[PDB]
Image (cartoon, coloured by chain):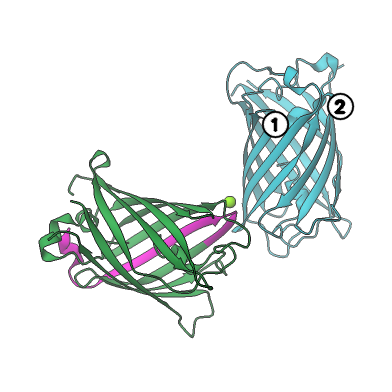
Chain colours: A green, B cyan
């Protein structure tokens, strides 16, 4: 699957959501450089104003795009499942607040890699950090601990995301993940190091998130 | 159990999830029903803010098991016979010269509370129409609900709702209904339900809401 990631690969992102009854849609376009672990994307809300903070959707809207080191090439499930693709599911627990359930498909559509997502948010508190938009427009660096999931012939990941709040302490989001192959069966413990930058397109009147991310793999000597 | 469950007053919880021309919203209602007297008292609230559609259009979509069937009609009602397991209630509502509603609901007992859970999708509603334009008066007329057996082992119903418009004209809503029992062994003749509704507001409620009082009795058989 490594052969399809050579050079620059186009990216398409689609998300459908419902948070405490609030529907919304997001569309993103950009490109990815798996060889260099670089992502550049621009997101727009096609339904108006986003009812939840943009940082909370960062993890939900890819991962093939990670640069796995030469001695770790065989451990990249994300790239190995292409072009057929894989299904990615999560339950995100915001401490003392609501929860997100997500289901996505990542696959090639022509020469474009597409990520179509469905998320449902429930039990979010009124005037909370999420529904109250009290989260800073930024993102911290994290470690995505990946482990094999023999039963589903895929992988599982666990990590806690730290969302900066406008005053000083931070809002935690526990992430639980499962990735499963879509077709024919081509596949150790390790982790991903992530860095993200959120920004704004000054000539865009629509709600915008501009994204730059750098991801590498490690954990094996 | 299935009629024995409705002696006296039963608590009610109602939940609706909807999408009209892309505008999702949710409504939650709580109240009580006294099937012996065919009476309902409920309060509904929009938990997502302002309703993108007029409240009266959601009345029929929001517990016919509380209808009052006469002693000589005990056999006839199917609503209570399907309890406590409950029944599925589906509808397609066509508003004349406007959009359409598709609904799916499950009505059943959860403990001592009768619960009605709903999904509603509205399509092809016109901009500046009576519906999306909020031109319907805050009231509800009396109707007759025509029920017939669907020996899907349930029932079907057809009727036309009359919504008063602010200008004085009326917006019609054709209702097509299908009910199927969730589990086993329920009762199935042609007859109708006579309905009366009263809409009001809670003076101390800032959220978009609707207070409803309803009286339903059955007839059509001598
Ligand atoms: Mg909904």
User: Is B70 situated above or below A2?
Assistant: above
Which is nearer the eye, B122 or B48?
B48
Q: Is residue A173 left or right of residue B96?
A: left
Residue for badge 1: B113
Q: Is residue A12 magenta?
A: yes
Q: Is residue B122 magenta?
A: no
The residue under the point 12% across, 61% down is: A221
Residue B29 picture quarter: top right
Q: Is residue A178 left or right of residue B214?
A: left
The secondary structure type at the circle numbered 1 is: strand
**Badge 2: how crowded within 10 Å, few (<14), some, or many (20+)?**
some
Residue for badge 2: B37
Write down the region rendered in magenta: A1-24
Q: Is residue B77 left or right of residue A97?
A: right
Q: Is residue A88 visible?
A: yes
Cα gap from disc 2 to disc 1, whole angstroms: 18 Å
- Nearest to N terminus: mark 2 or mark 1: 2
The secondary structure type at the circle numbered 2 is: helix
């Amino acid at each position: 699957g490594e052969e399809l990631f050579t050079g620059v690969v186009p990216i398409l992102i689609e998300l459908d959501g419902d948070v405490n009854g609030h529907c919304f849609f997001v569309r993103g376009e950009g490109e990815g450089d798996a060889t260099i672990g670089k992502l550049s994307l621009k997101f727009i809300a096609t339904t108006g104003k986003l009812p939840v903070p943009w940082p909370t959707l960062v993890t939900t809207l890819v991962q093939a795009f990670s640069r796995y080191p030469d001695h770790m090439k065989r451990h990249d499930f994300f790239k190995s499942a292409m072009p057929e693709g894989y299904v990615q599911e999560r339950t995100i627990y915001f401490k003392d607040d609501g929860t997100y359930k997500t289901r996505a498909e990542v696959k090639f559509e022509g020469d474009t890699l597409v990520n179509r997502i469905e998320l449902k948010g429930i039990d979010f508190k009124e005037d909370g950090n999420i529904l109250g938009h009290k989260l800073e427009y930024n993102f911290n660096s994290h470690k995505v601990y990946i482990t094999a999931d023999k039963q589903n012939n895929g992988i599982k990941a666990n990590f806690t995301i730290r969302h900066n709040v406008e005053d000083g302490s931070v809002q935690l989001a526990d992430h639980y993940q499962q990735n499963t192959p879509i077709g024919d069966g081509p596949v150790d413990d390790h982790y991903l190091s992530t860095q993200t930058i959120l920004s704004k397109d000054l000539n865009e009147k629509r709600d915008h998130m501009v994204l730059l991310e750098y991801v590498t793999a490690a954990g094996i000597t």
